[PDB]
Length: 73
Image (cartoon, rainbow, N blue to C red; front, side, top):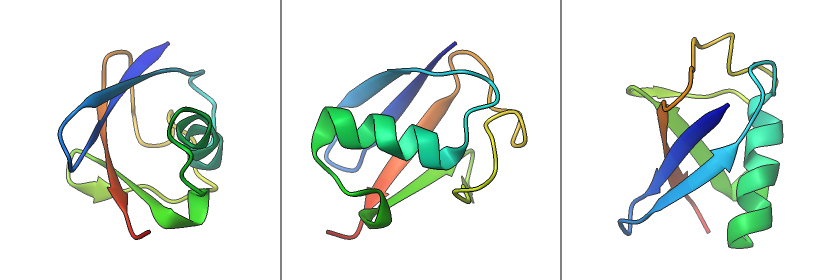
């Protein structure tokens, strides 16, 4: 299952995930690609900010869905 993540600076990060992954698991993939501690990340999907104990399938995040990464570093 592939999803995209866009950052305020511009660029896309593409992630390999699983439908039952937690948002915490998705932050840990972004931490692997970008060096950013999970507590400094917010992920927004279609307007709505994602909570770390919920899963992608909880929010109906499907293949080719786009998440927006917002930082407070």
